[PDB]
Amino acid sequence: DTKIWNGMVGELVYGKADIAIAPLTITLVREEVIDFSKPFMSLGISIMIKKPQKS
Amino acid sequence: DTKIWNGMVGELVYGKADIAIAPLTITLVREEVIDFSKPFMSLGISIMIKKPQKS
Image (cartoon, rainbow over all chains, first blue to last red; front, side):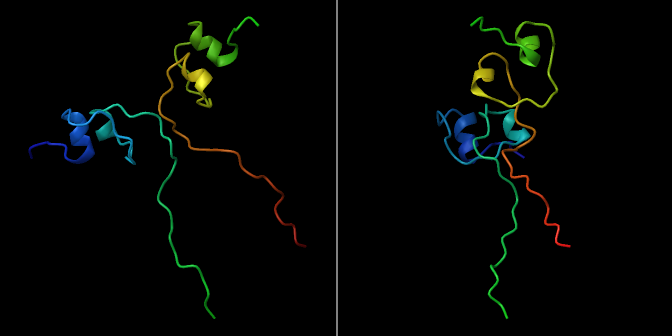
């Protein structure tokens, strides 16, 4: 409704913080508001299962 | 010696080509000469071995 970025984006868009050296997903809706650098960490959704010990 | 970029970089640095929609590794020595976009393809060195041919 109010279209207010909260969080670390709200500290960069609204001038509160100077830079965010933090784990932040580069999205398109966050691309237009702040300048991301290149991705330092390629990642994605992974499958956490229990390691097996069963019998 | 002559510090001349060949290849597709030499077509972008020396104005011959307009854009390179091509598989090109984003390196630092290529970052300073041309503007890369964000990486569309996370990749790296992989281990190609023969499939087990248990016959």
